[PDB]
Amino acid sequence: MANLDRSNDKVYENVTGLVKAVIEMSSKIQPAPPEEYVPMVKEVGLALRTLLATVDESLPVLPASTHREIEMAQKLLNSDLAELINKMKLAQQYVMTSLQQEYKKQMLTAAHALAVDAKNLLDVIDQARLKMISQSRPHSATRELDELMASLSD
Image (cartoon, rainbow, N blue to C red; front, side, top):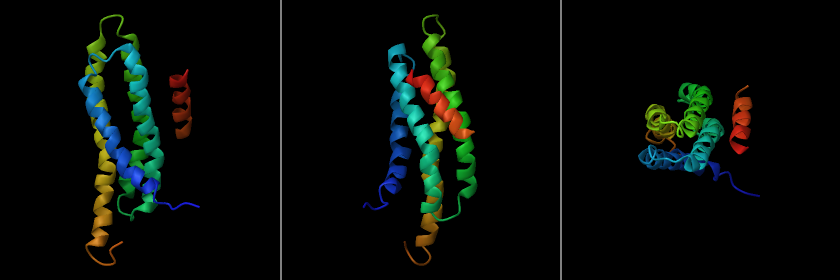
């Protein structure tokens, strides 16, 4: 047997951890070699795909109020994934040519907004849980994810 206080803490964790990388990687994104791209994109794909599930679990765990946001957050994750993996896989082949920093620039932009998203997740819903405390009684999507997963695996 085990309590259900494991994922509840992971949500507020990943939303932060994934962000930390978004910054660091964003610093060496330019010089980011083709050998460091494999793992780099791997991390992003994890927080992204995982976020879809994590967030879905945050819906019930948290008080209804940010359903709309969470709803659009799911679909967004899907598209974001492709766009992300794409830009990454691009620089991987556009490095031996010359257009390296190029794909890196446009990538940083999108990747930047994406990161903030995962953070705004708990940031938004937070207003719901808090609103409760300070008042009374203080207390084919998977297809793409799976497909892209293999594309990165082998």
